[PDB]
Amino acid sequence: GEGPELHLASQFVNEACRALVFGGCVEKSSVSRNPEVPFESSAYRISASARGKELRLILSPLPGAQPQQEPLALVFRFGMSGSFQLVPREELPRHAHLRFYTAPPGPRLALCFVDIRRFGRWDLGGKWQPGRGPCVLQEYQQFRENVLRNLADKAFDRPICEALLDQRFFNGIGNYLRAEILYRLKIPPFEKARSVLEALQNPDLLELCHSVPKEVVQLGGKGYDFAAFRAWLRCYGMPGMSSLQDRHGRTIWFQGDPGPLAP
DNA sequence: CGTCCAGTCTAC
DNA sequence: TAGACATGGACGG
């Protein structure tokens, strides 16, 4: 559920739906507590884009589609297990909680938001979440400036391994990326975030917040194969690696000294 | 076999 | 903040 996976899911949606025409209503599973999507069109296309840990999906009526209406945008958050799949209409995956159906005359497929653990959410409207920082993958320069010009914010009092999960400043970084990034630099997880980032402005911490997830995207791995990602990892859950619980109870994997603020 | 572990969101 | 939110598989005692 991290940046690279949201970004590959956007790629997948755009490639799978490039020729497809969808029709009818947007079908939510009965168990899902997310909002019904009030969009219905006789002929519409689906496109996507990702920003940090959010994915914007746009449902665009084709010319002359009925009823006459503007496009509708939704924003998804994947939680721990969210994903998109394109399947035959009659072979729906289990836990397909939101479904878009191709219209005739093509082979009848379904584009599904699949979410086993049901932690993901979707909203109506295209707005990104207002507090989130810029995307480490696609807004690198804005993201770098938003960290550095704000180092006096209380957020950077926390250990660097906890600050990397703060989506106001590291939108797209999650639990495996913070392990892999700190591991490249041999920076102890529980050194203070402000102290680590002041010692700055050999790629540095903020550069690696971009280049490391970019590597995952280049694998096509964690994609929307699973072994090429398992071999790419150097720290997260790897043998020989230490691990501690941060203050919110998430496991930080690291090697060597845990740092001064370790619990 | 029973336990444990695997990003926001909510409410006290 | 602390626990909730929730399914399934690996891992033990």
Image: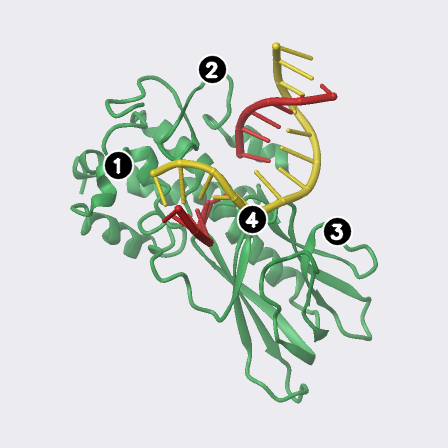
Chain colours: A green, B red, C yellow
Q: Are marks 1 and 4 on the same chain?
A: yes
- What amino acid is found at the position of numbered circle 2 in the picture? Gly
- What amino acid is found at the position of numbered circle 3 in the picture? Pro
Please rate how many residues cluster around mark 3, counting C-alpha atoms within 10 Å: few if below 14, some from 14 to 19, many from 20. Answer: some
Q: Are marks 3 and 2 on the same chain?
A: yes
Residue A34's spot in the image, x, y percent?
A: 58, 61
Callouts 3 and 2 close, C-beta under 8 Å: no
Residue A137's spot in the image, x, y percent?
A: 41, 51
Between discs 2 and 1, the one toward the N terminus: 1
Name the one closer to the observer, A30 or A198: A30
Please give left or right for residue A237 compared with residue C10 in the image. left
In the rendered structure, the residue with mark 4 lies on which chain?
A
Q: Nearer the viewer, mark 4 or mark 3?
A: 4
Q: Which mark is residue A93?
A: 3
On screen, A246 above or below B9?
above
Tell me the residue that label 1 is attached to.
Answer: A158
Between discs 3 and 2, the one toward the N terminus: 3
CA distance for labels 2 and 1: 26 Å
Between discs 2 and 4, the one toward the N terminus: 4
Tell me the residue that label 4 is attached to.
Answer: A119
CA distance for labels 3 and 1: 41 Å
Please rate how many residues cluster around mark 2, counting C-alpha atoms within 10 Å: few if below 14, some from 14 to 19, many from 20. Answer: few
Name the one closer to the observer, A59 or A94: A94
Tell me the residue that label 2 is attached to.
Answer: A240
- Count up the numbered dots: 4
CA distance for labels 1 and 4: 26 Å
Q: Which mark is residue A142?
A: none
Residue at (22, 34) in percent of width and height? A196
Callouts 2 and 1 close, C-beta under 8 Å: no
